Image 1 (cartoon, rainbow over the protein chains, first blue to last red):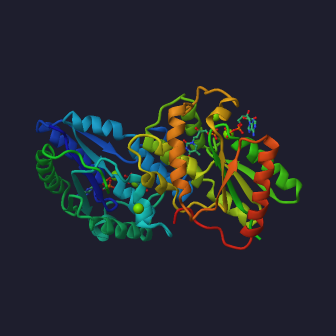
Image 2 (spheres, rainbow over the protein chains, first blue to last red; image 1 turned 45 degrees about the vertical axis):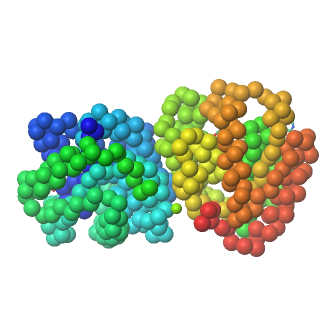
Image 3 (tube, rainbow over the protein chains, first blue to last red; image 1 turned 60 degrees about the vertical axis):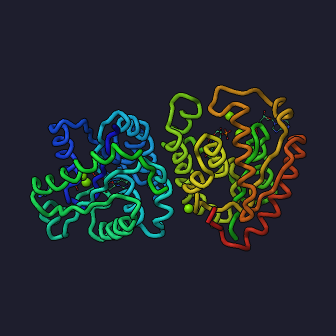
Length: 209
Length: 209
Ligand SMILES: Nc1ncnc2c1ncn2[C@@H]1O[C@H](COP(=O)(O)OP(=O)(O)O)[C@@H](O)[C@H]1O
Ligand SMILES: Nc1ncnc2c1ncn2[C@@H]1O[C@H](COP(=O)(O)OP(=O)(O)O)[C@@H](O)[C@H]1O
Ligand SMILES: Cc1cn([C@H]2C[C@H](O)[C@@H](COP(=O)(O)O)O2)c(=O)[nH]c1=O
Ligand SMILES: Cc1cn([C@H]2C[C@H](O)[C@@H](COP(=O)(O)O)O2)c(=O)[nH]c1=O
Ligand SMILES: [Mg+2]
Ligand SMILES: [Mg+2]
Ligand SMILES: [Mg+2]
Ligand SMILES: [Mg+2]
Ligand SMILES: [Mg+2]
């Protein structure tokens, strides 16, 4: 009985990391075997290059950094398929959708070109998109020193996320991330319990193919 | 008057490196501004990962290593376009075609998926493919300790190279690399002088788009 692959995507400060942590804690307390993953995975050789880039400690050519983000997913694919086949549900904080949206927000990058490197990745059984109005995101923090920490760029990435959501091949669910941390958690956890039960019924899919 | 982008591809031991070196030497002695490039470019952070992989000092997941090879090309794109626009002809020892053929030779990799990451790269004005029968390649050396150093795998990559050569968008020229080093050089140098003259007439193209 395979585990489900559940991805959290969403606007800045909507709570992807907070909710992915709480979801894994809650699923394990309810008897599930569940583990947390995130992308970028900064612990690998490629992950260190990406971390330096995002921190602005280094500059990387836009196409090159897009492919490194994708490669950083591919290198975890053997582990992801092993865990899922062992019945472990994986809760992932960002995935290929962030990959496509963030490069897709840059000038002269088509969504098609941006998608290709990730075609074939393990297909999420559930993609949660945490929505939050900017007035509410503004009370949760201030723009940082990191790469992409600006409103004009996050808006362009948001348009790309909406283009991706038109893809009916994927089990997208919108989450109203403006509620309390607990209320949002409950919405996500109930959606996750449903997906976990149905994932044991269909083989793990392939993304965008 | 832009420089030309000339790529050398070919079967193992056909003489890509020998001929790319001699071509750059000959073009500069004939008054051209010409420089040598090669892929993988092992000097960068990504290039070091690729070098370790090819030397079998490390293992890399097949998709991940394919994207790193492509990224290693992208990171040199700003330099390539700068040199070409300055009138410098660039002679390159392997390019995206090797990228697609070598991953394409592995099981479960379509030529389509393999091509995507390199779509958009600076398009070669001339792609030379050095052909050599295996009996003749056999007298030029013995299989090494490196990755891909085996006949069954080189044969699969060779089929992929022939699929790529069906692409009429590209100025492919076959070279009979079985002749002497000097005779092959002369064949390549005359083809290169012709391409250099015509490249000053059309803008640098984009590969596979
Ligand atoms: N529903 C929520 N209500 C109020 N604050 C929240 C909520 N979700 C997250 N936060 C706070 O907002 C900040 C951003 O949360 P985080 O999970 O790191 O977001 P993301 O990973 O989407 O950037 C954190 O300080 C977190 O405590
Ligand atoms: N035309 C040729 N005739 C005879 N030996 C050659 C010829 N071209 C290359 N060689 C030798 O064969 C070997 C492989 O050449 P090299 O240029 O390194 O090939 P490649 O880069 O295609 O693997 C080298 O020792 C080189 O000196
Ligand atoms: C996974 C992923 C993240 N990103 C970005 C989004 C964030 O700006 C950044 C750090 O992620 P975080 O907000 O999850 O800490 O990485 C990409 O640009 N491409 C990718 O493939
Ligand atoms: C450029 C390139 C080379 N290769 C391989 C072909 C050779 O086996 C190897 C070393 O190159 P070399 O024979 O030019 O020294 O790298 C790939 O697998 N992918 C690539 O994108
Ligand atoms: Mg986060
Ligand atoms: Mg396509
Ligand atoms: Mg951040
Ligand atoms: Mg060589
Ligand atoms: Mg070698």
